[PDB]
Length: 49
Length: 49
Image (cartoon, rainbow over all chains, first blue to last red; front, side, top):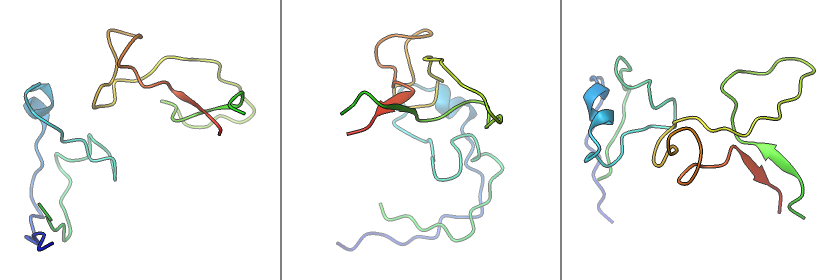
């Protein structure tokens, strides 16, 4: 109910070996593209973990 | 009546006045597919309820 609002943005979502790592859970963002994460800079993305 | 099937996505974009009768799937994410085709492969066509 008090979900977070940390502004984790304007960074690099590097995923090259992250995708290869099978132990990883999930990183594909269908909002824009699973591949469009490396050089994508996030405007004001807020995490609600 | 599920006899009507429509495509979910195509690797290439539209091309005017063309028909596609393919059934393979692309390695997208989650459980993309096995080898080239088979189980854990999301069908590229969905029917209409």
